[PDB]
Length: 38
Length: 349
Length: 141
RNA sequence: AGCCAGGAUGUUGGCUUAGAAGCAGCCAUCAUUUAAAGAAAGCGUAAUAGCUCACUGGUCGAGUCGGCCUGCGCGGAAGAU
Ligand SMILES: [Mg+2]
Ligand SMILES: [Mg+2]
Ligand SMILES: [Mg+2]
Ligand SMILES: [Zn+2]
View 1: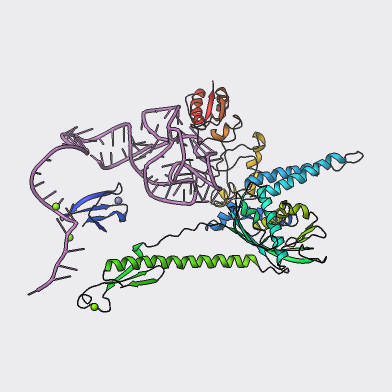
View 2: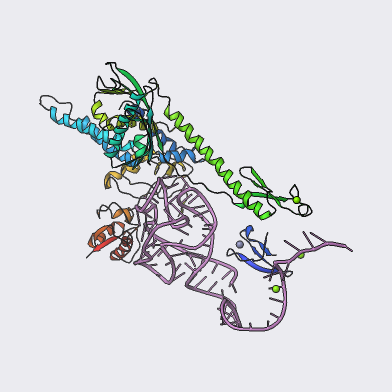
């Protein structure tokens, strides 16, 4: 997990999901692409 | 071909062992050996096709021999002459398959005294003529004259193409045997001169004052300052992490001034520590290139009474001293390279 | 039909066995023998010419016995001795590599008309010249 | 958007280099069969291979797809009795 003030899509598998009032990125291909806004 | 023929003949089988190791599948799991084979594919397929041409010439030589009763001498005479010509052409074209920059030529007097200075002047004139008949520029960086004749020590800078590739074999000592000009009797005397050849290098001096690798401490100073000096951080200390050089300053009452001048001192005294290293490196290199001119360690001898010049590295003597002293020393430096390069391809193991 | 298993068409001109990297480790990683190409592969090379770059199927099993079927030389190397140019482009618009007559290509297309797909023979001309334009080959009117 | 099917042909290209083949970097970016398919957008080889996408056919079957201007909110947001 990488925590940064600007989460963005990096590949074509990345998805934007808002869980519990937090915006975060997850993709099913590259585990290095998961990130949350903080 | 003294041994390059033997070098290739021993290595000609390696030109097939590389192919053998190509198709074994035991050198394919790794990469280094296969890379070596691919780079050394049998005499480099361009030169390999050249070798096929030479073998066609050799096969043409092989025929037209088993018949008699004909005055046939001239055609196979010219045929074998052409074969030798193309053989030497193959030699040079596969020997062609770095350090080609300006040079510093330094020559000084060895044993002999004034006669050594005279011979140094003559030798420098020879090199200057060889350079001027090459479209090269020679400039006298420094001179120390020799009282009667030439120079105690002349150092000049030669600018051109491939200068160091041709002049790098002139280092060492040169011996001269002749009747000197500073001699009342007719006695023959032996003297020596010492010659060094150097390349030129970039001399960047990067001020690594990059603060990403500095450790800085601020603290109180010591002395007579009353109540202000106690409660203030007016002393600075900077350590440069890559080199371990430490400098501190507390001379003034202002932290900013101390930091500025301490940083300046750090820069100066980190630049000196590199200039000294470069100086000692170049001095050491000059020392082991120069030798100690004492007419016992030498590379070539000039006998004026016999008009002969001999080279002891390759054991080659010639009777063309006058043409050499007028600046046609090319015939001396061609064979040496011929030997020297012949070892560069051999040292691949 | 069995699809590609262990064979990729890649090797130098058919002229001889030439036990070089293009042939040795082309099969060395897959098996068989390097020297075998002088008898079976080169049986038909005496028919055509010495120095024709053609790709040959190198189907090899785990049995280390291989069968080979060739094809026509690729159009790039095909129109080299027929065009007199040994080099090729890479800057075919800044300059050009030579000249070629339009009539010189269709009379060799029937060699490749069997293994190339198209409505008729004349259709093969357009495919080559479009490729030929990439080599800087200027059509001679 | 899903769900089935296809997703083709001479570049083993000179151009660089040992090896570069759509996918390392220098140019060009045509043509054929076709309903479609890029002389290659992505993953993947020392080099091949191999793996997706575009695009095109069948079921489904009612809506669906992105910019512009604006109101109020979300994160970015850590200190000492
Ligand atoms: Mg939770
Ligand atoms: Mg005082
Ligand atoms: Mg806010
Ligand atoms: Zn992703």
